[PDB]
Image (cartoon, coloured by chain):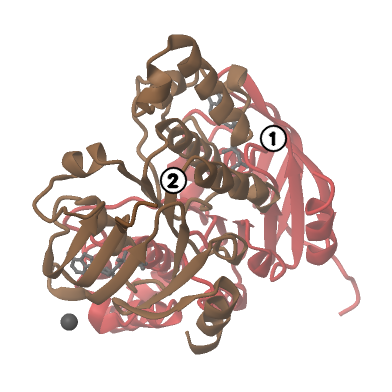
Chain colours: A red, B brown
Amino acid sequence: GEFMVSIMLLKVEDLHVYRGNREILKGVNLTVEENEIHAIIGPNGAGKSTLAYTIMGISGYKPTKGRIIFKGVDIIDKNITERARMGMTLAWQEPARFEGIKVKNYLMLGMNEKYKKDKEIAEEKIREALKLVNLDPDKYLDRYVDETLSGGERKRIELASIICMEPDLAILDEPDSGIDIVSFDEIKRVFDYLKDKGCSLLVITHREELAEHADRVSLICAGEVIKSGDPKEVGEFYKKEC
Amino acid sequence: EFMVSIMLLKVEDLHVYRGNREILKGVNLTVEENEIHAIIGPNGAGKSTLAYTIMGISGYKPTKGRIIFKGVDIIDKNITERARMGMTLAWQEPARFEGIKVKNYLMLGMNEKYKKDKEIAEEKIREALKLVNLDPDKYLDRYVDETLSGGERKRIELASIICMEPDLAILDEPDSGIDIVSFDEIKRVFDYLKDKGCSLLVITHREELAEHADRVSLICAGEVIKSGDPKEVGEFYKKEC
Ligand SMILES: Nc1ncnc2c1ncn2[C@@H]1O[C@H](COP(=O)(O)OP(N)(=O)O)[C@@H](O)[C@H]1O
Ligand SMILES: Nc1ncnc2c1ncn2[C@@H]1O[C@H](COP(=O)(O)OP(N)(=O)O)[C@@H](O)[C@H]1O
Ligand SMILES: [Zn+2]
């Protein structure tokens, strides 16, 4: 291979986002490459979740200045459904509970077409995803994705949902939240498995254990990317300056 | 010189069944007056279930054993009866009570020693926000709703505990959603609460916070496996679990 190029999957250009009265994002320049794990670190109120919501096109999160480019398309006038059709997904910090929806049915919703095309393949995929996040398929398939699950179990089911979905870009807002340490290698193996399939993860995290697993980390302070690059160097700068 | 000694909280061989599964299988746990007792352990071990059973949350009734708070068996007392005795619970993922400003939220539940004088209560709310690093002038008139970030809502919940100043504050992951550059402020909140005579029963996944407790208890499959020194119990957890 002669040329060494980099492909951009997502490009956030000088993004200014106003929430209510306050200016949360003040010119964010962020890129996500194809098959890359890009972690976003920073203090509370810096605008990390707001950045994820603006990329997903959550109602109310429209930029006043700048633009979001996904797969070379300017997605500014596209609703959350139009962005999800292109291969983008968001995992919330506290995922929704649903009465009456079983775990098997929830993991089937959003499953990649390459698995849905054959019933037996889709059933094996759900079992594989639960085993990846350390949940016994025979104990959790019949459970409901409701208030009965513990936060850690719900967070693992959300991660299994991403495996089945196999999206082009998975934005994960604190995928570690509520999950015990000891289970942190399983989270890294999920990220590795997703990278192996061609996925790109944009992970917001407070765990250095997970942020150091990314290929690139970006520090965000007061709606601005302060530093970006090596996970350990950017992490050390965070723990000392901003 | 008064020999009458009363244990703040005493959980005796507690067996709790949730749905079909037996979550707690004989829990023996005690909380002393003016003590920070951390509870560590893997997911599904029953730590949150233990906190909900102590608070008397609807559906969390024990099949065997008993819960004794301030020498009183609270088994037949509802969550409101337990809260009047000085017990409180800070849920992991707190409620967004819309149409209620942060000033009203912090005033609901405030300790009587502060409510008795309007000026004292107004200074208490400002003090609590400053303790959790929130600027009172920026957050006092804000609404507790989805507008607040998880870290901000978790800090407001901690400020609420300062104003309340309870005898026993059960905190289910008080660190969750809070950045690591603010973990000293969480420890200073625990110190401030201990200084006032409060006892905290903190469930946590951060060794940073669990090592700040006077005693840590490891729970595995509804059972206390080890208890005592925070560093020794913490090392045993990473090793065997
Ligand atoms: N409607 C609104 N009115 C006022 N302030 C608002 C708002 N919606 C959001 N905010 C504020 O904007 C900031 C955005 O925080 P967030 O993007 O969640 O920060 P983070 N996840 O990186 O911790 C927070 O300080 C939040 O309270
Ligand atoms: N109604 C229910 N049916 C079945 N299982 C139930 C249940 N309510 C709770 N559980 C289970 O109880 C277990 C205890 O979870 P929890 O007490 O939150 O554990 P933890 N805080 O230490 O992470 C979990 O594995 C959960 O799935
Ligand atoms: Zn027993």
On the question of residue B173 being in view, the answer is yes
Whether discs 1 and 2 lie on one chain: the answer is: no
In the displayed structure, B125 sits above or below B184; it is: above
Residue A166, given in percent of the width and then of the height, sits at 49, 68
Judge the density around disc 1: few (<14), some (14-19), many (≥20) Cα neighbours within 10 Å.
Answer: many
Location of mark 1 (residue) = A67
> Is residue A147 visible from the viewing direction of this image?
no
Residue B30 location (% of width, % of height): 34, 65
Residue drawn at 23 percent across, 61 percent down: A148
Say whether residue B85 is left or right of residue A16.
left
Task: Say above or below: A39 vs B97.
Answer: below
- Residue located at (64% from left, 67% from top): A210
Residue placed farthest to the right in the image? A2
Q: Residues within 10 Å of mark 2 (few under 14, many from 20)?
A: many
> Does residue A59 appear left or right of residue B50 in this picture?
right
In this view of the protein, which residue sits in the foreground, A43 or A203? A43
The residue lying at 17 percent from left, 58 percent from top is: B60
Quarter of the figure that contains the N terminus of chain A: bottom right
Query: Which residue extends farthest bottom?
Result: B240
As helix, strand or loop, the secondary structure at mark 2 comes to loop
Instruction: Give the SS element for disc 1.
Output: strand
Image position, residue B49 (x, y; %): 27, 63
- Residue B198: which disc? 2
Amino acid, disc 1: Arg
Cβ–Cβ below 8 Å for labels 1 and 2? no
The subunit letter for the residue under badge 1 reads: A
Which numbered disc, 1 or 2, marks the residue closer to the eye? 2
Please name whichever residue, B218 or A21, is drawn nearer the observer in this view of the structure. Answer: B218
Quadrant assignment, res A142: bottom left
Q: How many angstroms separate mark 1 from mark 2 (CA)?
A: 50 Å
Q: Position of residue A67 (x, y in %)?
A: 69, 35
